[PDB]
Length: 340
Ligand SMILES: NCCNC(=O)N1CCC[C@H](C(=O)Nc2ccc(Cl)c(F)c2)C1
Ligand SMILES: *[C@@H]1O[C@H](CO)[C@@H](O)[C@H](O)[C@H]1NC(C)=O
Ligand SMILES: *[C@@H]1O[C@H](CO)[C@@H](O)[C@H](O)[C@H]1NC(C)=O
Ligand SMILES: *[C@@H]1O[C@H](CO)[C@@H](O)[C@H](O)[C@H]1NC(C)=O
Ligand SMILES: *[C@@H]1O[C@H](CO)[C@@H](O)[C@H](O)[C@H]1NC(C)=O
Ligand SMILES: *[C@@H]1O[C@H](CO)[C@@H](O)[C@H](O)[C@H]1NC(C)=O
Ligand SMILES: *[C@@H]1O[C@H](CO)[C@@H](O)[C@H](O)[C@H]1NC(C)=O
Ligand SMILES: *[C@@H]1O[C@H](CO)[C@@H](O)[C@H](O)[C@H]1NC(C)=O
Ligand SMILES: *[C@@H]1O[C@H](CO)[C@@H](O)[C@H](O)[C@H]1NC(C)=O
Ligand SMILES: *[C@@H]1O[C@H](CO)[C@@H](O)[C@H](O)[C@H]1NC(C)=O
Ligand SMILES: *[C@@H]1O[C@H](CO)[C@@H](O)[C@H](O)[C@H]1NC(C)=O
Image 1 (tube, rainbow, N blue to C red):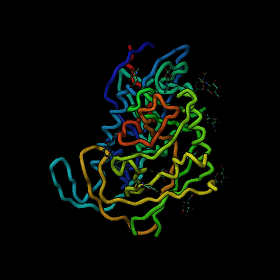
Image 2: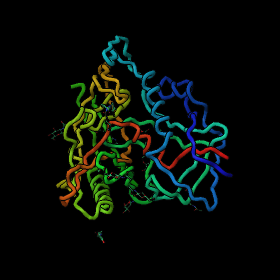
Image 3: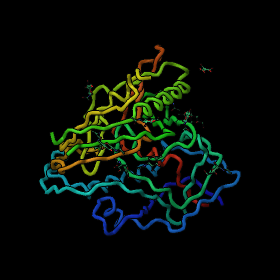
């Protein structure tokens, strides 16, 4: 086998149920084929292959699909786009993301990096060959990566360029921390409950590894100062409702009487600034009854402060906004090649 680096158009696969009215299922039913009934991963003996997750067309290809999925699935009362106005009907929908596999057409194959502490760029010593990735959930998230994969060994610090502060940092956790968000039976007041013990343990480890990457320096956490509500809050979609949660308690540099349950204040918003960058959208009020989503915190989005080269500290705040990094967090060990 001999290959070369190449971009090409991918296709998708799913376990989607054709009887479901859930929108991820309805979209995967007509845009994707069924998942590979006999998937086989094959090792590449004595092969070293270098990867670059910040340099992967797979990401932008998935991004186009999630844009597609949201525009056909989400029914907004009125669509406020670039100097435009549209008025429609906005019934409530069934919303729950399902895993999606990304697969190469003929002449192309996917290379899988299996080195347990691969950071996302550079040489991979344990390389695989697959026809499709594994099932990736398209979770649209800010500040915190939800329902993803875990790093198998240590916590991984991923970044295209650690010395550039504009570059986003992806923290790949090795132990998931549960986030339990509930709007109980304001109709827009909600809260997310987190294990403080579990949470502070893991964030202590996150700081000890950023210490390794930044020359033993003091690692400070801080809430985002300024930006849109989707940036300064942990924003996610639970069962169709847009949750905005205040995470200041999570990035508490201190509980590093504070090892119980952390309860984050949340509000469901009807008017959101779309992650697709095209403007404002207005949706309908929340459904009646108890609205609950439990998810796994599996990764953290961070931006580092600048102007601290002559200081003794480094400051990191929760990031968000560019959903590409969310897909990048799960496609990092994949790249497409052209077989020669
Ligand atoms: N480093 C990139 C700067 N990002 C940026 O400029 N954006 C434009 C304005 C806010 C946009 C957004 O994140 N929207 C959103 C909507 C719903 C959910 Cl659930 C969610 F998690 C997020 C992103
Ligand atoms: C390579 O990765 C595989 C799959 O993750 C795993 O069995 C092990 O870590 C590695 N195996 C060899 C033979 O290097
Ligand atoms: C990732 O590993 C490569 C070596 O392959 C190194 O050059 C790069 O600085 C590392 N990046 C991070 C963020 O650790
Ligand atoms: C949450 O994480 C555990 C392991 O940490 C895993 O077994 C479980 O399936 C995860 N749940 C979801 C919804 O991903
Ligand atoms: C997670 O990684 C840290 C180092 O980053 C390590 O100390 C810890 O033991 C790991 N935890 C698990 C459950 O692997
Ligand atoms: C990373 O960013 C720093 C500061 O922005 C810059 O000086 C450096 O050349 C960049 N390195 C690479 C490899 O792009
Ligand atoms: C999530 O929280 C609600 C109320 O806060 C509680 O009733 C439920 O048992 C919790 N679920 C889990 C899995 O912790
Ligand atoms: C937090 O996790 C610990 C283990 O780290 C566990 O014993 C305990 O049940 C959890 N506490 C809460 C309040 O969820
Ligand atoms: C960083 O601190 C650790 C503390 O365990 C020490 O072992 C290491 O030599 C230090 N390295 C640098 C570059 O300061
Ligand atoms: C989050 O809560 C703190 C107090 O707990 C408050 O000062 C801060 O303004 C809140 N964040 C936002 C974005 O409103
Ligand atoms: C994460 O997965 C669980 C189980 O599938 C689900 O209940 C929860 O709503 C998911 N979280 C998000 C943010 O989609």
